[PDB]
Image (cartoon, grey):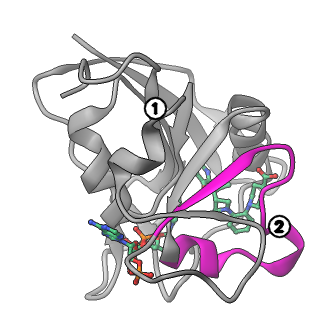
Amino acid sequence: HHHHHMTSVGLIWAQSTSGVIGRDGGIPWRLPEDLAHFKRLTMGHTVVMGRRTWDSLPAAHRPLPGRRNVVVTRQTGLVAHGAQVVGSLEQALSPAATWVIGGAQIYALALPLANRCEVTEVDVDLPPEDEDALAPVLDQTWAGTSGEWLVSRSGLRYRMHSYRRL
Ligand SMILES: NC(=O)c1ccc[n+]([C@@H]2O[C@H](COP(=O)([O-])OP(=O)(O)OC[C@H]3O[C@@H](n4cnc5c(N)ncnc54)[C@H](OP(=O)(O)O)[C@@H]3O)[C@@H](O)[C@H]2O)c1
Ligand SMILES: CCc1nc(N)nc(N)c1OCC1CN(c2ccccc2N2CCC(C(=O)O)CC2)C1
């Protein structure tokens, strides 16, 4: 349903090579270069996230500055300030390039509607654990390109993949 709307809908996430995106209510690695990449791609745009991701943000970073923060929840509203709440992904997207920034539940809702995915792969050894949030799997409707492996100042290797709907 990526052509049920006019504005581009992009998913953006970072994952380990094993496909983990979240653990224990947070992200189980630190990668400053990915944060800068995420900031450059999203600055000045609407960012849409699930409520658990909203609550996972450290207070210094909530709301994400310089972006319209939209939080998808079934609740009437939120205790933590700075978001616009909506009750569905469709309400998040219209009116409106909108970035869906996680987590796994909101990626699953948005994947059928998305035109683009921007993935950072982090070469950190994290065998998936029972409660982990995992990255969405991309099917045959996506075409991708991949950048070279880069080395972070902290020593972790990482790289970016970019997918567009065929
Ligand atoms: N690595 C990355 O790039 C990345 C990015 C973002 C997040 N994360 C990680 O992902 C994890 C959180 O992901 P998650 O999947 O547990 O949660 P999530 O997708 O962030 O949020 C789930 C919440 O969204 C709301 N929601 C879900 N489906 C809905 C629907 N159909 N209609 C309305 N509201 C709906 C509900 O909020 P209510 O309960 O309020 O109703 C639900 O509890 C954390 O570990 C976080 O650190 C990682
Ligand atoms: C940087 C992590 C990330 N990476 C890619 N590639 N995709 C994503 N969806 C993604 O999750 C973005 C959300 C979760 N985040 C976060 C989590 C923990 C500590 C700091 C942050 N934030 C605060 C605001 C900063 C900003 O000003 O942008 C960015 C870092 C914002």
Which residue shows up at 63% across the image and 69% down it?
A: 29
Whether ligand 2 has any atom under 8 Å from the Cβ at mark 1 is answered as no
The reply to whether the magenta stretch includes residue 71 is yes
Residue 59: say if magenta: yes
Residue position marked by numbered label 1 in the rendering: 10
In which quadrant is the N terminus drawn? Answer: top left
Q: Earlier in the sequence, mark 1 or mark 2?
A: 1
> Label 2 crowding class (10 Å Cα cut-off): few <14, some 14-19, many 20+?
few
Please give left or right for residue 106 compared with residue 57 in the image: left
Disc 2 under 8 Å from ligand 2? The reply is yes
Looking at the rendering, the quadrant in which ligand 2 lies is bottom right
Q: Residue at x 61, y 83 (%)?
A: 78
* Percent position of residue 141, x then y: 14, 21
Q: Position of residue 81 (x, y in %)?
A: 77, 77
Point 86% across, 52% down: residue? 65
Residue count near mark 1 (Cα–Cα under 10 Å), binned few <14, some 14–19, many ≥20: many
The number of numbered badges drawn on the structure is 2
**Distance (Cα) linking label 1 and label 2:** 21 Å
Q: Secondary structure at mark 2?
A: helix
Q: Which residues are magenta?
A: 52-72
Disc 1 residue type (three-letter): Gly
Image x and y of residue 14, in percent? 52, 51
Q: Please name whichever residue, 11 or 71, is drawn nearer the observer in this view of the structure.
A: 71
Answer left or right for 44 relative to 99: right
Q: Amino acid at mark 2?
A: His
Vertical placement of 9 versus 18: above or below?
above
The kind of secondary structure element at disc 1 is strand
Nearer the observer, 62 or 151? 62
The residue that disc 2 covers is 61
